[PDB]
Amino acid sequence: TRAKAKTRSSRAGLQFPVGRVHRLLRKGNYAERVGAGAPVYLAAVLEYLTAEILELAGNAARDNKKTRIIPRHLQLAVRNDEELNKLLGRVTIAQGGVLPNIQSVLLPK
Amino acid sequence: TRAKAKTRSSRAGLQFPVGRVHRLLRKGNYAERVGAGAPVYLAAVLEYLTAEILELAGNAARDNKKTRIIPRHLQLAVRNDEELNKLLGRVTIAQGGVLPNIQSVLLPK
Amino acid sequence: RKTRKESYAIYVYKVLKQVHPDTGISSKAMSIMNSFVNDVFERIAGEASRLAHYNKRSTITSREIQTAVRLLLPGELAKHAVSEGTKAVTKYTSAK
Amino acid sequence: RKTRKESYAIYVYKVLKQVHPDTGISSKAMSIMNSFVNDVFERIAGEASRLAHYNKRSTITSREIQTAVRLLLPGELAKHAVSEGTKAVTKYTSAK
Amino acid sequence: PHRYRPGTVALREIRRYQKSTELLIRKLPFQRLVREIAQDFKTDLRFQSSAVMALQEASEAYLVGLFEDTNLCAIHAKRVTIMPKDIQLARRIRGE
Amino acid sequence: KPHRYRPGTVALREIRRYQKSTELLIRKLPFQRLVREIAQDFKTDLRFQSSAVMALQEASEAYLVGLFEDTNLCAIHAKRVTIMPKDIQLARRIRGE
Amino acid sequence: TRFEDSPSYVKWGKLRDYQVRGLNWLISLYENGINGILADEMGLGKTLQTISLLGYMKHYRNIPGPHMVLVPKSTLHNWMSEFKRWVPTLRSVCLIGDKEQRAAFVRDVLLPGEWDVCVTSYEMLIKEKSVFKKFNWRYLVIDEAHRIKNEKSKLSEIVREFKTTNRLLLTGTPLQNNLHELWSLLNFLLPDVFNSADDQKLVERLHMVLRPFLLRRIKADVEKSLPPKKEVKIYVGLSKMQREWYTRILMKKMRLLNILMQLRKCCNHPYLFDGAEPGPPYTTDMHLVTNSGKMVVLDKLLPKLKEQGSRVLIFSQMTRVLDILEDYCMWRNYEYCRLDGQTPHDERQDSINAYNEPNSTKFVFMLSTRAGGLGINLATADVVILYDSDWNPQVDLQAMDRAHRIGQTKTVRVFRFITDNTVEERIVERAEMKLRLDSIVIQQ
Amino acid sequence: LRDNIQGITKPAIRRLARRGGVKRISGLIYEETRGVLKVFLENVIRDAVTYTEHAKRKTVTAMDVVYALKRQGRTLYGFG
Amino acid sequence: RHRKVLRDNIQGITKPAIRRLARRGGVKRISGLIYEETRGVLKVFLENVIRDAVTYTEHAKRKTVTAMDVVYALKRQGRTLYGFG
DNA sequence: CCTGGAGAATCCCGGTGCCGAGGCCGCTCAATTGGTCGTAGACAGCTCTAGCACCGCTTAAACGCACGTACGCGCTGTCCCCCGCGTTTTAACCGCCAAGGGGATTACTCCCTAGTCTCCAGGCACGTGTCAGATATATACATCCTGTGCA
DNA sequence: ACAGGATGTATATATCTGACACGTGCCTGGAGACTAGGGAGTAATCCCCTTGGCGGTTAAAACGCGGGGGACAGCGCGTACGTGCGTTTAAGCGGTGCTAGAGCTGTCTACGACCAATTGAGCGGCCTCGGCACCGGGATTCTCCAGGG
Ligand SMILES: Nc1ncnc2c1ncn2[C@@H]1O[C@H](COP(=O)(O)OP(=O)(O)OP(=O)(O)O)[C@@H](O)[C@H]1O
């Protein structure tokens, strides 16, 4: 007899796949061995970052009167936050556009 | 009995440690298997690069009327050479100084 | 049928419905999120690999992941990330 | 007795004697050359590792090393280094 | 007759293009340029449409950032019109 | 009556002299004290190897020298000879800080 | 084996039997080709013996060759004056000054070579080593031999690099912390004898191997004058504020990397620290004295001394509290004299000697373990107060026997204030064990 | 054929500048922009062609372009 | 009573030292407000580097910052230093 | 030189099609459970190396101050270059079709690399001595800057 | 516009020293020989997706033109920095003393790799509908003359 299959993500109460993260860690040639808690830690971090960016994008979409998040909303959210902006400083988001700003000298006198 | 030991560097005509490079490739977590030709090729490339930089540095040291090579000579060789400058663009050489240059607008006239 | 591809799309959708219950996401935005997750995974895993090599060890552990998170993420993001990971590992060990 | 430390010093010295027979090198210069060789080795090895992962292959070969050289080295250096590597592999295969 | 002052239409265009998010260069000319550049490196080379789209996206982002830095330089020089010297100063400070 | 050089010659002489020499220009002890003060905030009870402080000083000096090069370029761009905080800020903004 | 009385070439000579027999001993060592240590512990004198030896060398078989004497910079004027007023017939030069002055002096004196003895300091010796090596040295005199007591020190290696026909060492306490520093001194003396580092193993071996190359005698058993000093410890307790300071610092922002040092002068005085140092300089009034039990004890002792001698001379360990107490005595309602490392070198020798007065009614002089050199006896001093003790008992011995020269024909009392359950107990026990080692090695 | 850099037109360069945020444009900017675009594209296309030739293919893919851009420090999100 | 603080450590970076750095860079005339700006820039740079180095040292479970830690931190920030390990 | 209208351009409200997002199904492959075993690292123990708190002496370097001169900065005129608008031409754009190349998948075989055991020489640590370089010192050259005539 | 004077600098010479190059001993990691196994090469097949073309349309580019504002050169000024000179200070080097802490050794366990069997989680394939794009019309707002303020 065997118990019902409980996922490690279920054990940690997460939404990201601990099993998939573990397989990616093992098949990526990062080290000889991978401990039991490292996939859980990494999955929690990935979930936190995803939740942050999605919350900011959802607020941006609410300000723009829509219900679907698009790359423009993602770009607005990422460039309007300083921490995420420094994290993604060297990244281009396709179909993202630019932040509206005009240098105050170009405005008519 | 067994044959007399020939180093693979001697086999390839190189003067760099093919065996040590093979060990480092295998222990560095870059893949699971390593071809025999890969350490030979890597050692050949390293040898060419080292010879080039050393030749430029020796020319600079002779221009300075010296028989030893110091980090100043190494920096003076790396700069003034385009390919090596691009290769070492983001590298600081300790106690190597700066290229001697003055913008032409600062010269009195 | 064609060969299977992997992605984080279902989990991204779960987190989206968790944080904002009445919002959807387009395919291009989902592709962007997938590439973002892949890139962050790559950065953290590579930093942990470098740490393990530097300290002359052969096991990636939670301490290495925590140190890589400290190195890569700035400030309050790092504080919250460390707290979240610690809660996750604590609960996983407690309920195991 | 201190633990032994491995370095490329003797090989750098041999190459120096080959290129400028009546010339010497300083200890700081040798440390700089040591770090330079380690850096180049790490960059080329990492590029080859990523190439192999991209192509779903598990072995690093002379093809991967050549492609890494072409990607990382600017132009004429790449051409000459590729010639050197071809000659070395040819010699290692022809009679060894 | 109604003619706007020389510079209001420019600000209207600035606002319009900073609110829009779509490409600005024409796709067929960009594709022909990409094939012209690829002609030197290898003969009879085929392309995917996604590759050309990604190349155009990256080119546009790079040029937009370049122009923003150029505007900063020109404003520093107490001008309003950007110049080749401003472009070259931006490139030199970036590191080309 | 005593000999004086006109403004703009001793500066050029110093430029050549320092662009030729390779010594470190900041005094070692004040820099070490500054490094210790900064490291005190992150984590108390810290010791430093003497080589670590020298590496830090090397990196700091190289960074400042490159920054001053770019700042000089900005100042020359503005048709000036004197560098200013505006030039420093512009150089840092373009380099991405 | 030589004359029993002073030679007829000394001037103002009053050297006694001990000094004349030491001179005979040194001359015999020179005749048989043996160097050594003139381990004259105390007032019996070593400058007189060294000068008389060199003068005998000149005034007997002609050896006018190079001779060098090494002194601290605080004794250059003293040594030159002693040479002038004892043996004027001998010629001496001094290498002192900035770079230009030193170059001028060597150029105008050293290379012409009209000199016979050159008096230099350690620092100038290190400066002009290449200049001195160009000479065939014969006799080398090093005062305070514990300066070179260890190898791997620049001065010791430099002074070994010199070549002399003869060597000679001068010290007060050759043994300080262990037998290896003494072995270093003996290695400098005779390189080719004590090449190796190595109850029967020691004590007897040390005596039998040191008798040929050393002379040891005690002023108490030689002069029979100079009534012995009486040493009394005062066991004090630390106030509650000091106790909580001590406990908190021991169990724990202010940088704290050295537990022993940071928990040291605590028993001395809390506000010697930083962080909670006295804040706004309101005024110099009754603030510092009330905070320390040792300060209370000293403030109680002062009246009992001023109703009597009132010429104490005080000792403490930390240069800060040294200067604090120095500028405090003047304020309180007293007067002082100044001796510390800040004072420019040449001015101290005349200043302190001048301050030695028939009467001062100033009641205070302050000297630390490292604020003074070797001279200026305070025969007017009566009481020695030691606020805290140094690790090395030899430093404290030098400090407390500084006033125990001949001038002191009166018994002097030394007071050692000590606290409880603090690091000072460890300091005291280490000093006692080191002193016991020194006694068992030398006296026995 | 040839002469396709002229396909990058003055109006397109003006639109790029207006998205950047500039108001007035000098007449000589256009050739400079064409030159810098040519340099950037040449670098990226050379890297992509190297990747494709290593793969032993004849078609250049979005994966190749993305890998080249990531190598240059210009990571692109939204293509895989 | 004698107890006070002399100066702050950021003032250890001296005006003639900054002028020597500017001379090596290639500058001829220097405005008076450059010095505080340079001190601030240096403080920011050192805070970043020291944070990363202390992170590495803490992972090692040590209490002494090493040259290797400084080199690893500098390579992380993208300023590879040759000649220290 | 503060107001008041034209007149373009923009935002807001409502209706229509449509196409991609989201829900739903089967299926297969990858994650889970269970058990076994070897090794990596945790833990304790000792050595000795190196770092921290501190003093004396030298002396270079920093600090402070006075004088003058380039230099940054503000203001003005000129003119020329770029912008706004209208018109004509060009080609991108879009929709659809046709064809072949080539990327992707499957099976089969075999050669190359992992792992082992042994042995031995190449590389490392340690001493040691000698020369390349830094140092000082006195010439000869180059550079700047002022001052007296007449350009 | 040069002559000359004072300043700085490049150059030749002699000494002395510490760092580098060479040798010696020794040991640990690489080379030789072998055996198994699975990853990659090779062939063959399929289908999708890239290219080539063709026509109709309309947005976009190219060209011209007038005119206003911004760039650029000039001039004046009054002030902030460079240069030189005296005085103080703190860095640099050297010793002192101490103890922590980094580094190597040995033992032992508990933790992760490996394997086998099961099954449910996720992925490709479908379909339907609501969110979005487009289109149109009215209300609103900003800009630019022109005048009377
Ligand atoms: N002319 C003299 N006659 C007799 N005794 C003298 C004479 N000069 C010096 N002394 C002795 O020297 C003692 C003090 O002299 P001084 O302090 O100069 O001694 P020192 O040679 O420096 O001794 P130390 O060995 O302690 O360094 C006197 O107490 C006395 O014993």
Image (cartoon, coloured by chain):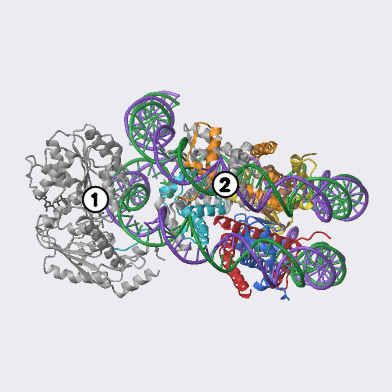
Chain colours: A blue, C red, D orange, E yellow, H brown, I cyan, J purple, K green
Residue marked by disc 1: G344
Q: Nearer the viewer, residue K140 or G32?
A: G32
Question: What chain does mark 1 sit on?
Answer: G
Q: Are marks 2 and 1 in contact (CB under 8 Å)?
A: no
Tag 2's secondary structure?
Answer: helix
Task: Give residue C70's mark.
Answer: none
| Residue G65 visible somewhere in the drawing | yes
Where residue D24 sits in the image (x, y, percent)?
A: 49, 35
Residue at the image point whose x is 29% and y is 74% from the top: G239
Where residue E11 sits in the image (x, y, percent)?
A: 67, 55
Residue marked by disc 2: D38
Q: Nearer the viewer, residue K6 or H23?
A: K6
What amino acid is at disc 1?
Pro
Q: How many labels were placed on the picture?
A: 2
Residue J56 vs residue J70: left or right? left
Where residue J109 sits in the image (x, y, percent)?
A: 81, 48
Residue K84 vs residue I41: left or right? left
Q: Nearer the viewer, residue E23 or G89?
A: G89
Query: Please, is residue G115 above or below residue E71 in the view?
Result: above
Q: Nearer the viewer, mark 2 or mark 1?
A: 2
Q: Ligand 1 closer than 8 Å to the CB at disc 1?
A: no
What amino acid is at disc 2?
Asn
Quadrant where the N terminus of chain H lies? Answer: top right
Where residue G3 sits in the image (x, y, percent)?
A: 8, 42
Question: What chain does mark 2 sit on?
Answer: D
Dot 1 crowding, Cα within 10 Å, few <14, some 14–19, many 20+: few
Tag 1's secondary structure?
Answer: loop
